[PDB]
Image (tube, rainbow, N blue to C red; front, side, top):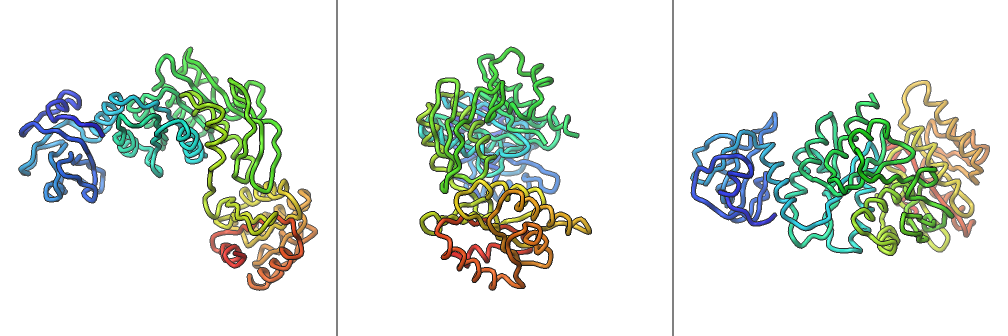
Length: 439
């Protein structure tokens, strides 16, 4: 936040001042988050009118109240027509007051990893702020934007959308120098929505999109004549490319080719899909100045989310890939592809999937057949359905409990000096136990 006076806000938020003037230096919508003499914005959701929490905010030390009606609270009030709007507007205003290179992103999948990778890289460049958690809606964006100060050098704003019109609002507040749509997944309506992100770009702004997944046909009417950047590992029209992809026991090594040159980087996250994210992140970072050196160093310190292709170094050359969070045909079939490229003797350790009905048997068979065709060295399984996988893989063995698996697994680990293990199963299968047990 920046210091602002109630009288200045009457103009800014188009609202009436009903009390003395005051300087604010902090604003919040949460009673559990009051600061001495801050502005308490009383929002009204459907199942909550924070106006009824006015007295509490006063009692907490709130200096004034931003509200949509007069309240009998001995505190300077700023009566505006709509608080949802005013909150966003106040955030818009604050963002205009700071010198931070603001950049934004959306998509159907990967918003968080592209955000985190972009933030990780720009952090090598200067003081950077990024969206916290999944605060990407009409309330979360203002909250994120409101955290800005003259001390920030960069700002990575993640924008989410559920319906149309939503991103249009938030980018108007954010006014990013570069905007990115990571991907799409009816579909045209989602494309229309995410495409809205390009409307907040200045005339010198850069529109970035996925060469392998976009809606340029329609997005060109909103990006207009602005500069355009495309990322993809090998797309013909890609600006951010990935060559010499060599998967290692650590992560993926590759030559990242950007519009200014290339740098051989090490992406420490299992999964080829992270290579694309890294390209998006490189694009976003570079739009606001990041150097190749900054990109390489930013990527190099990424950490995976436990239970999701989470690498765990057992001993030398003994890699465990914790992907025990959940599992369905898609994520499972994909897991096999990840393992298949891994170094050494590869063991797919699995448990039942969260599949439904008569197609369950078939779904396990497929995954087995996939590991079979992938050349997986061995598949140890537990469950009353997962036998289908190990059976179909033409290799591997099945167990009646996880304890017998862990034992045979440990032996295999001691037996094979170079092994890559991938543990994965449905939530109900509780495969983390195999992972815990191993470490």
